[PDB]
Structure formats: structure tokens, C-alpha cells
Image 1 (cartoon, one colour):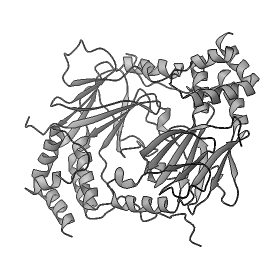
Image 2: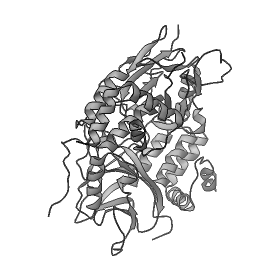
Image 3: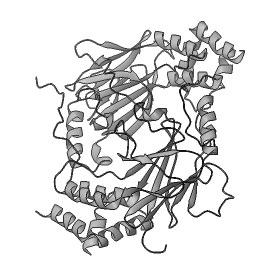
Image 4: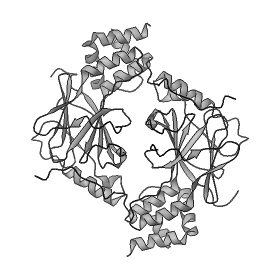
Length: 42
Length: 42
Length: 203
Length: 203
């Protein structure tokens, strides 16, 4: 659910397609996800 | 009228200010007016 | 085939430097940059018709040449995703050179990354290095990952010469990659060089 | 200070190469590019407030430096017409370099035409050579006269690096000049070089 959390930090408008494509890259690249989480917690 | 002819040959929209400023440069430079006239004929 | 694996592309076209077209497209078959009618859907990929230069230009010489390379696009420039790669192919008669670079500038002269192949498809972008560079960007490397694909159509890639001299330049942006880098910026990553010297009176 | 020396200007500002502001303004007193509140209207010239980078950007580092530069603009960069010349004067703390260039690319590295003076005004555009070049442009040359003034603010002129790396760039175009050159193109003049070499298959 850090998924949904990262998405909401987007200022710019996005399409359902774009969101799903961002989501798929995130949920398939945990090392990238941790990087974003670490950015919020460091 | 000759000046008015040159103004018509302008694709882009324009403010009354812009148009007047163009006309002022035309009235002040007869050799430039000649340049445009010679361009459309010979 | 899995929903979300295909990519949404923002396609922006530049005739002689001037932006003349912009559209965001998302479909599984990818894109085909064409310059004419679409009564020939024998080819796969969504046909993106590049506009006639008469709609936005006044230079007759440029309009004539731009019209020519557009007409010679034929099947067009194909671009789609398969696996971790972005694939491109030149289906017409216009030699097309590409480079991955900055969003706002195709840049020169580090030269084109290569020429878009004709007979077979060629890989033009790898998601692999992107993600790796995004992570280190998040970790404060200061170097933002490139995701903008620029295509020079009909002419040699503009080295040393300004890209605005080219008749037809096209930018394609995977919007999901743009969003990822933005996520890093919002997270606190910056691209600002430490060599910035502000010229401001201090005395 | 009353006759026909009012020039309408299109002002376009770019933060880090990205367009964040554009307005077309015609004022007999000319312009003052500022970056804050306008309670200082004791100064002549229409005050053009450059936008806070929070409205458009996500890069925090860039946002900080842009905000600081805009802060130091003070009285701002002044621009007005008197006679055959365009005059500029730097009223604040931000050093400002200028060049007459293309409409789309401030270009490099032929160097900046100069630095906008502070203690006194300085001419940054002479209408004379423009009209001379305009006439020759209509006579079949390929050289289109330049009328776009670019201003680099708070940093040195981008002489090697891409101009998109500069924090605050501003382009100012006298719309009447733009229209004149457009009349030439409509008249039949073209900027297309004879060195154009199309890369199109012939088999």
C-alpha cells in the first residue's frame, strides 16, 4: 500500500493507463520501491 | 492602402497596437515598403 | 500482453524547431509515426499522423521540404514495448536517427545513439539502466536518468548544427518514466549542479 | 516620451529551460521584469512579475535557486524603446547578460552580446541593421534578421553548457518585428539553407 502512497505524491495529472504502468514498474522492482521509501525516511 | 495591403498579408492574429507599430515602421521606411512591393511583383 | 506493460507515449513533433503537434497515446500495439492517410491499416501499431506544415508555418521553402519527408514516411516510424526494451523500426524511405536525451533538448554534438533499422527491429531504450540510474538519483547522485527519445527524420542527426535547423524532429516520452523521475524529485532529488555560480551583487 | 515609440512585447520566461510564463504586453513606458510584489510603483515601466517556481517545478534545488534569483531582481530588468534603439537597464542585484538571437534557441557559443548596464541604460537592439537585413532577406538571401532578445539572469551567459541549465532565462520579442519578418516569408522569402541534404532512400 506504499504503492498507493507513492502515486499520491504526483503533482502532475495522469491517465489510468499511466498510473497502471507506473504501478507495474514499482511492484516489479522492489529495489526501486525501497529507494523511494528510503528517500522519505532518510 | 498600399500599407493596408501589406497588413492583410499576415496569417497570425494581431493587436491594434502591434498593427499600428508595424505601420509606423512602414511609414518611416519607404525603402522597406519598396522591398515588399518588389517582392510580390517581379 | 499483461495490462499496464504497454506504455503511454507523449509524442511531440517539431518542424524547423517549432512545436506543431502534441498528443498523448496509450495502446498495446505501440505507435506508427506517419505523414498521410490511413486507409492502409495492414500494419500494426496506432498511426500517429504528423500534421501538414501549412497549418502552422509560413516559410514556403520549409513547408515544401517538410511535406516531402512526411510523404516519404511510408509505413512510418514504429515504436513499441516488448520485455524490458523499447523497440523501433523504420518502415518507410526516410532515414531516421535517434538518441536518448534530455526532455527539453536533443543536444549536440555527442552524436546519435544509432540509426533506426529497417529490415529488422532495433532496441532503442532499456528500462534496466534507467531504473538503476533512478535509484542512484534518489540517493543524491545529482544525475537524472534519461527517458526522452528524440528522432531525426529525413536528415542526418544534427551534430554541432542546432537541432532547430532540422525539418522534422520528434520527441517521444514514456509518460510513466517521466512520472517516476518526478516521484524522485518530489522525494527530494535534485539535478542542480554544484558548479552553479550565481552572479548577484553581494557588495 | 509621448510619440510612436511604444513597442508591444511577448515575454517568455524559462526556469531551467522550461517555459513557466508568457504574456504579450504593450506599454508606452516599456517593461520591468520583476519577481515580487509591486508596491514599488514609483518606478516607470509595466512591472512583469515572473512566477514562483513552485507553480511549475518539482525540483527543490532548482526551486530554491530560482526563488533567490527572483528575490534579488529588485527594481528588475528594464526594457523600453527610444528612437531606433531598444534600451535595457539592470536596476536590481542580478547581473544580466543579453543576446540578439533566434526565436527558439539563444544559441552558443558565439558569446553574449554584452551585459546589461546598471548605472545607466544601454542599447541592446538597433532597428537600422534589422531593416537592412530584412530587405536583403526579401531579396532572396537565406539570412533572416534576428529580433529575439534573450536574457540570462543571475548567472553567466550559457556559452558552452545548454541554455536549459540556466536557472532563469527570458526571451523578449517585439511583436511588430516578428510580424515584419512573417510578411517577408509570406512574400516568398525562405530561411532554408542550400546545404540541406535529405537522407531518403531512392530505391
